[PDB]
Amino acid sequence: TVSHEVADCSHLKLTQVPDDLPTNITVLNLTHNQLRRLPAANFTRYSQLTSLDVGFNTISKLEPELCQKLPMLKVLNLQHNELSQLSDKTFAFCTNLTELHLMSNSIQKIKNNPFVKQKNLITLDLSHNGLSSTKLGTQVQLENLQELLLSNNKIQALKSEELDIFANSSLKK
RNA sequence: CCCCCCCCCCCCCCCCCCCCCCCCCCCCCCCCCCCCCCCCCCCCCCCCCCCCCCCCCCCCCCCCCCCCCCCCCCCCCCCC
Ligand SMILES: *[C@@H]1O[C@H](CO)[C@@H](O[C@@H]2O[C@H](CO)[C@@H](O)[C@H](O)[C@H]2NC(C)=O)[C@H](O)[C@H]1NC(C)=O
Ligand SMILES: *[C@@H]1O[C@H](CO)[C@@H](O)[C@H](O)[C@H]1NC(C)=O
């Protein structure tokens, strides 16, 4: 796992997050591994991560406290996992996120408000899920959102109310 | 009891590209052989023509000699 300013762990057969890395590491790439979970305790040492690419692993669920240990996290990639369920507290503490990638997670539906808390989010990706609607919330949030990816889902119609949460959003894509 | 999503490794097949290796064809150059045409040099051959030399033949010319025939002239002697 060679790392001078960015840490990469691609195809390293890793099952748990390594605990021997420089403290000032800002980028942690853990793609194509066997990470079952991402406990917050394993990320206590890393308090300066900006981008955490954990996609192409076997994560089934996360914990909100993980975002507590990463106050400066900007890019969070959860591509190709099985996080089929989300909660309103899942992304509450991740208030400085810019990119949130959730492609190919077999998510079936969005319940109440998983993205209300974050306000600086720029792009939200939800492609290759089982979503049958564009409903992502109830109130108006995602003020600064510019890109919304909803490709390869089960959406069959577009309704005005389902998009009402983007009243103050200038969707560039 | 039953699905789906990731990881490594092993493959199979179809394309692309790069390697050596070889084949066939072609090009460039050189060499060799053969054929055709042409030039140059030297030694000759045959024929024709011109000239020259030697020898010979025939004819003719000039001169000379010999013989024959013919003519003229001189001496001398007889006959009637
Ligand atoms: C973390 O590393 C992975 C693997 O290198 C990156 O994912 C993809 O890697 C493949 C193979 O090198 C590339 O062909 C893709 O282009 C990469 N994806 C993208 C979106 O470029 C992954 O991007 C890395 N993550 C970060 C945050 O750098
Ligand atoms: C955000 O949306 C609300 C409700 O529509 C509106 O009152 C408010 O003016 C919007 N904000 C901006 C900056 O336009």
Image (tube, rainbow, N blue to C red):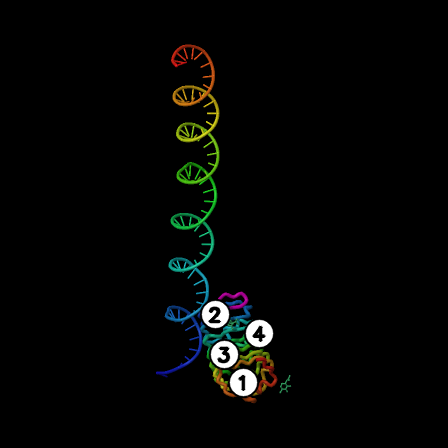
Q: Amino acid at mark 1?
A: Leu
Q: Secondary structure at mark 3?
A: loop
Callout 3: CB less than 8 Å from ligand 1: no
Up-down: is B66 above or below A38? above
Q: Secondary structure at mark 4?
A: loop
Q: Amino acid at mark 2?
A: Ser
Q: CA distance from mark 3 to mark 1?
A: 15 Å
The answer to whether dots 2 and 3 both sit on one chain is yes
Mark 3 residue crowding within 10 angstroms, few (<14) / some (14–19) / many (20+): many
Instruction: Measuring from the top left, give residue A139's x and y in whole percent.
Output: 58, 87
Q: Which mark is residue A10?
A: 2
Q: CA distance from mark 1 to mark 4?
A: 25 Å
The answer to whether dots 1 and 4 both sit on one chain is yes
**Mark 4 belongs to chain:** A
Q: Which mark is residue A103?
A: 3
Question: Which residue is label 1 attached to?
Answer: A136
Q: Amino acid at mark 3?
A: Met
Q: Which numbered disc, 1 or 4, marks the residue that appears first in the sequence?
A: 4
Tell me which secondary structure the magenta stretch mostly adopts: loop
Q: CA distance from mark 2 to mark 4?
A: 23 Å
Q: Which mark is residue A173?
A: none
Quadrant where the C terminus of chain A sits is bottom right
Magenta residue span: A1-10
Up-down: is A52 above or below A109? above
Mark 1 residue crowding within 10 angstroms, few (<14) / some (14–19) / many (20+): many
Q: Quadrant of residue B19?
A: bottom left
